Image (tube, rainbow over all chains, first blue to last red; front, side, top):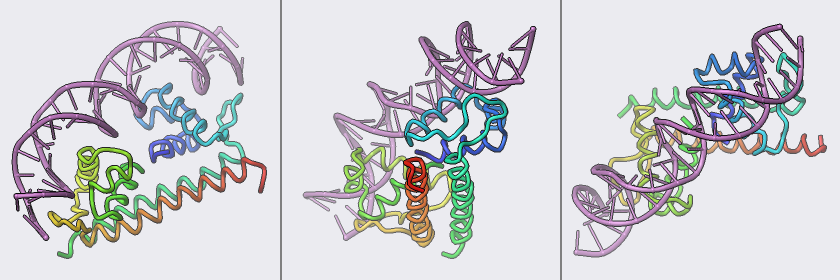
Length: 89
Length: 90
DNA sequence: TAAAAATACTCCATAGGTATTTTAT
DNA sequence: ATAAAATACCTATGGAGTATTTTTA
């Protein structure tokens, strides 16, 4: 598990398309699709419904998404706050 | 950045040695150093002091450090709960 | 001075790309 | 029929290794 997997996962959910996700992320659709499989096979959990356009989360997906964005958000504050402090000497 | 960078950094700080943390993480010391460099380099900050046997954080480090340990703990939480749901136990 | 951290490469595992097929409209 | 996702294969960036040179206690 890396932030990469989350950020990728989040892009899929928000955008409801590996394609549109892959565009926004500036990578191709397959490698994206593989990183999602990887995430899932690592958790042994199915995060996205297979067999439907648009692309929708499973109950577990939705739970995970919720903690994903909150957790990515927290990384971003962690970095900001840290930079402000590097101006104290 | 990535969780690898955090976990590594945390390891380092906890051991107060790159060398001790290296094999703690089952990797070599030199790559470790580089990862920690890139981290500081990406943030454009100095998270560790520029030289001390008992290697210790800067202020920026300490803050990051504690926050890091909270985030990694978050990732664990996230995984446990999802797992917990997936397993069929609410 | 003798430990521990930093270079200077080498190697390879794997994230990312290309071509094609399969599935779901 | 036709676009998007899945599958297979290939490439190449950077994570990890070995040998070696700085460091600072």
